RNA sequence: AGCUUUGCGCAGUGGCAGUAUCGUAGCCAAUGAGGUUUAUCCGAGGCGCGAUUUGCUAAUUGAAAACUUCCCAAUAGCCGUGACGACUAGUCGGCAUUGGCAAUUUUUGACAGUCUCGAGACUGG
């Protein structure tokens, strides 16, 4: 259902933001371009 | 092969964000939520409770705003004077420091403005 699409997308995106900030936390790269 | 539809995912431009976006593990819900319009019609979530990550930078207070200071002593132009020295009371060279260096020949400013085709003129009432 569409609410489950929103929840699955938002939790995949939350772990995606979490693992990008995780790879910033390890210090492999400076953070991406802010705009 | 190209066009294209629908759903989903990714990224990007822009817009919106407390009558917005959600969670709900409590209950109810297409075996029908919720309906004053059109009701022998419409058809999706509803009621409560509960929310509103991360990095960077600025500014303020504060003694201190969190990534491995202050203080004393000494060293880093010339005219005179004192010695030392040199050359004939005088002259010269270097050194030293116990006064001075804005009144025509110099270092405390006759300068400033104006106009004309490298060169001159005007004014400072």
Image: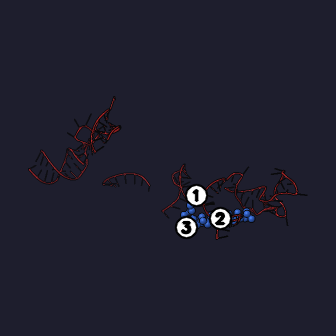
Asked if marks 3 and 1 touch (Cβ < 8 Å), the reply is no
**In the structure shown, which secondary structural element does the residue marked by tag 3 occupy?**
loop
Name the colour assigned to chain A in the rendering.
Answer: blue
- Tell me the chain of label 2: A
**Precedes in sequence: disc 3 or disc 1:** 3
Label disc, if present, on residue A35 of the rendered structure: 1
**Precedes in sequence: disc 3 or disc 2:** 2
**Precedes in sequence: disc 2 or disc 1:** 2
Task: Name the one closer to the observer, A20 or B54.
Answer: A20
Chain displayed in red: B
User: In the rendered view of the protein, which quadrant contains the N terminus of chain A?
Assistant: bottom right
Q: Nearer the viewer, mark 3 or mark 2?
A: 2
Q: Pointer 2: what residue?
A: A13
Query: Residue at left 65%, top 64%?
Result: A14
Using the image, determine if residue B87 lies above or below residue B109.
below
In the image, residue B84 lies at what x, y percent? 16, 53
In the image, residue A25 lies at what x, y percent? 57, 65
Q: Pointer 3: what residue?
A: A28
**In the structure shown, which secondary structural element does the residue marked by tag 1 occupy?**
loop
Task: Name the one closer to the observer, B34 or B73.
Answer: B34
Q: Residues within 10 Å of mark 3 (few under 14, many from 20)?
A: few
Color style of the picture: by chain
Q: Nearer the viewer, mark 2 or mark 1?
A: 1
User: In the rendered view of the protein, which quadrant contains the C terminus of chain A?
Assistant: bottom right
Query: Residue at left 73%, top 63%?
Result: A2
The answer for how far apart the CA atoms under marks 3 and 1 are is 21 Å
Taking B51 as reference, is B121 left or right?
Answer: left
Using the image, determine if residue B31 lies above or below residue B121.
below
Q: Residues within 10 Å of mark 2 (few under 14, many from 20)?
A: few
Quarter of image, res B24: bottom right
């Amino acid at each position: 259902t569409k609410k489950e699409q929103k929840k699955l997308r938002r939790q995949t995106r939350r772990e995606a933001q979490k693992e990008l900030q995780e790879k910033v936390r390890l210090g492999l790269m400076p953070p991406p371009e802010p705009k």
